[PDB]
Image (spheres, rainbow, N blue to C red):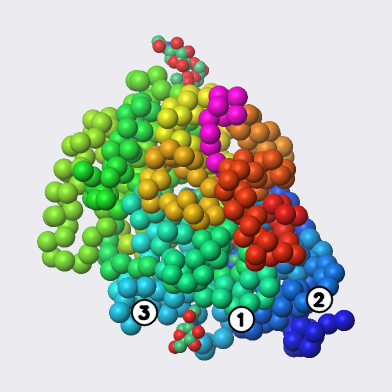
């Protein structure tokens, strides 16, 4: 027996069971796992979301799990609702009116629908001379999707993750109740939802902090053959000054294994063939099995004196560093071209047929005290003698910029590294080898007693999720699940309560 508001969605053709609808909502970016839903909802408004979730809340014995598909960038089925209902979030942004992205009158924040993609949040913000302060490396992800994880990039050391740059949200709980939440209003829901893995409700609107939009980014790469010098410099560039930070707007880093060195440097799209020859000769001279590169930017505007001020500011910061003499490499681009840089890698890989392939990505947070051990056992150990396809990203984060009361789990140390090994299974049937190598890396960290946290991964065992949050923080997560999704129907693909 269906409620009238739920039956109206099927009448209006918003609730589909056809093979085309279910097939599209059954695969994700990871391209490793698949799960067909029973139905797909294409909501035209937030009232359609209220109708589905209230039906779920009031119907006794309701058997359908519900997932909120952003862009399906999930790696291991986190956006699937096996034999359930997948919400096609993008349908909320179909009409020309009402607008889904509103920059505030005062220009201090930006209101964006949960379904909206960060690239559109950027374009709408830039039209009003503003931009969010904390980003992901890839802009074709949804506001609600990244906020359900953390949302990290080279800006998070100073501005914190995307979850630390949200003023307020509109959420529809598992009870079908539309609640506006912040630190001052319904704080418990606001904190549970940020990094909440879609467990407590759907974010329909997020109010994102903005800053005056820079016009350009001075973009640098610094080369090292010594991991200790590389990691020490990343920490210097990202350390809090004796609340204040250094001038860098973005700090990331990358690891290049010797075996494929020339090809990998040439594939960054940053280095010229002359730059490549020099770094390859440097590696041979130092007899390095690994090469490290700091990637950093300095944001600046259209002011007449800006270019010279940046040259001086950059010359000053570089003098404090310990990269191999003469191995500083500069580029200067428009701010939006820098932010949207990964979209170019997508275009080039898609035409080669190397984008829509399995992505057995390994993403983790490694405490600073164990990063050199990780480098020895992984970059200089396990990954040696292998053909790597995908970037190996390493960069420090400041725990002070993360709110531990939110759902997102991080290591206890003040400084911890985001470690992103973006393996693409390009070779014929290389998937099984990559999945085993990820199990080996994790086993190496477990045996060495490294207290890491995974990021973007879903655990399949209860004991793993309990260790992921930590026992006390886990009990708190359960408290919020009981309050907001007692029926355990939301985002079943996380495998926390399903
Ligand atoms: C594929 C990809 C992912 C990625 C990235 C680059 C690429 C090519 N770069 C990232 C980066 O630099 N930093 C970062 O923190 N994450 C990065 N990612 C991962 C990305 O954040 C995740 O894939 C995330 O899931 C966002 O993707 P998407 O927007 O496509 O969301 P989804 O996969 O469909 O769903 C994820 C889970 O969240 C729940 N969900 C989705 N939308 C909502 C809303 N509006 N409200 C509540 N929950 C929501 C889903 O149910 C699912 O469980
Ligand atoms: C870095 O990797 C390269 C392979 O690209 C190694 O260079 C090869 O080494 C073997 C063994 O002496 C030679 O037979 C090949 O002809 C070399 N190839 C090229 C393209 O130069 C090199 O040994 C590696 N360095 C380290 C420190 O492992
Ligand atoms: C945290 C995370 C998975 C970041 C991913 N970033 C990227 N994802 C995919 N391709 C990339 N190239 C450079 N950076 C890339
Ligand atoms: C992965 O993508 C390929 C090519 O688009 C497709 O044939 C296959 O169904 C996908 N597999 C999974 C498990 O999603
Ligand atoms: C944007 O503002 C309009 C009013 O101008 C409103 O109807 C709409 O709900 C807003 N969109 C978001 C995402 O807040
Ligand atoms: C170069 O480094 C390799 C790999 O670590 C090692 O086998 C070899 O002893 C080194 N050669 C010299 C001359 O140090």
Instruction: Report the number of discs.
Output: 3
User: Where is the C terminus found, in terms of image quarters?
Assistant: bottom right
Looking at the rendered structure, the secondary structure element under dot 3 is loop
Given contact means CB atoms under 8 Å apart, are the residues at marks 1 and 3 in contact?
no
Highlighted range, magenta: 445-454
Where is residue 6? Give x, y as percent: 76, 83
Q: Which residue does the numbered mark 3 point to in the structure image? A: 104
Looking at the rendered structure, the secondary structure element under dot 1 is helix
Where is residue 48? Give x, y as percent: 67, 82
Relative placement, left or right, of 236 versus 465 is left
Q: Which residue does the numbered mark 1 point to in the structure image? A: 46
Given contact means CB atoms under 8 Å apart, are the residues at marks 1 and 2 in contact?
no
Q: Which residue does the numbered mark 2 point to in the structure image? A: 59
Q: Relative to the observer, which residue lies in front, 476 or 271?
A: 476
Q: Nearer the viewer, mark 1 or mark 2?
A: 2
Q: Residues within 10 Å of mark 2 (few under 14, many from 20)?
A: few
448 in the magenta segment: yes
Q: CA distance from mark 1 to mark 2?
A: 20 Å
The residue that appears at 68% across and 61% down in the rendered structure is: 482
Identify whether 480 is placed above or below 51. Answer: above
Where is residue 59? Give x, y as percent: 81, 76
Q: Residues within 10 Å of mark 1 (few under 14, many from 20)?
A: some
Q: CA distance from mark 1 to mark 3?
A: 21 Å
173 in the magenta segment: no
Q: Earlier in the sequence, mark 1 or mark 2?
A: 1
Q: Is residue 370 visible?
A: yes
Q: Relative to the observer, which residue lies in front, 459 or 291?
A: 459
């Amino acid at each position: 027996p269906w409620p009238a508001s739920l039956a109206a969605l099927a009448l209006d053709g918003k609730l589909r069971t056809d093979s085309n609808a279910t097939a599209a909502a059954s695969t994700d970016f990871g391209n490793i796992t698949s799960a067909l839903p029973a139905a797909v909802l294409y909501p035209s408004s937030t009232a359609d979301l209220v109708a589905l979730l209230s039906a779920a809340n009031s119907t006794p014995g309701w058997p359908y799990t519900i997932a909120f598909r952003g862009r399906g960038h999930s790696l291991m089925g986190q956006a699937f609702a096996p034999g359930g209902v997948v919400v096609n979030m993008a349908s909320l942004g179909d009409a020309a009116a009402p607008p889904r992205i509103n920059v505030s009158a005062d220009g201090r924040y930006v209101d964006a629908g949960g379904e909206q993609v960060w690239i559109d949040v950027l374009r709408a913000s830039l039209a009003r001379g503003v931009a969010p302060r904390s980003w992901t490396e890839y802009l074709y992800l949804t506001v609600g999707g990244t906020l359900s994880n953390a949302g990290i990039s080279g800006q998070a050391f100073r501005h914190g993750p995307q979850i630390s740059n949200v003023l307020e949200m509109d959420v529809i709980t598992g009870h079908g109740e539309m609640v506006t939440c912040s630190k001052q209003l319904n704080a418990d829901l606001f904190d549970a939802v940020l990094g909440g893995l879609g467990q407590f409700g759907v974010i329909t609107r997020a109010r994102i902090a903005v800053e005056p939009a820079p016009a350009r980014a001075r973009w640098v790469r610094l080369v090292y053959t010594d991991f200790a010098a590389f990691s020490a410099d990343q920490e210097r560039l990202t350390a809090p000054r004796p609340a204040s930070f250094g001038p860098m707007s973005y700090v990331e880093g990358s690891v290049f294994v010797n075996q494929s060195l020339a090809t990998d440097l040439a594939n960054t799209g940053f280095f010229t063939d002359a730059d490549v020859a020099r770094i390859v000769a440097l590696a041979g001279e130092r007899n390095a099995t690994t090469v490290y590169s700091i990637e950093a930017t300095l944001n600046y505007d259209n002011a007449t004196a800006a270019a010279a001020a940046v040259d001086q500011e950059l010359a000053s910061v570089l003098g404090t560093l310990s990269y191999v003499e003469g191995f500083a490499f500069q580029r200067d681009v428009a701010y939006a071209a820098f932010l949207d840089r990964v979209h170019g890698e997508e275009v080039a890989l898609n035409k080669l047929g190397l984008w829509r392939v399995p992505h057995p990505w390994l993403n983790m947070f490694v405490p600073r005290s164990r990063i050199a051990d990780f480098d020895r056992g992984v970059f200089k150990g396990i990954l040696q003698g292998t053909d790597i396809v995908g970037p190996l990203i390493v960069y420090p984060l400041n725990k002070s910029m993360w709110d531990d009361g939110m759902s997102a789990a991080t290591p206890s140390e003040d400084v911890f590294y985001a470690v992103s090994l973006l393996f693409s299974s390009v070779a014929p049937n290389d998937l099984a080898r990559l999945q085993e190598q990820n199990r080996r890396i994790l086993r190496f960290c477990d045996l060495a007693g490294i207290q890491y946290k995974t990021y973007l991964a879903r655990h399949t065992d209860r004991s793993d999720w309990v260790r992921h949050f930590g026992a006390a923080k886990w009990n708190r997560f359960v408290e919020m699940k009981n309050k907001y999704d007692p029926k355990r129907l939301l985002s079943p693909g996380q495998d926390i309560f399903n």
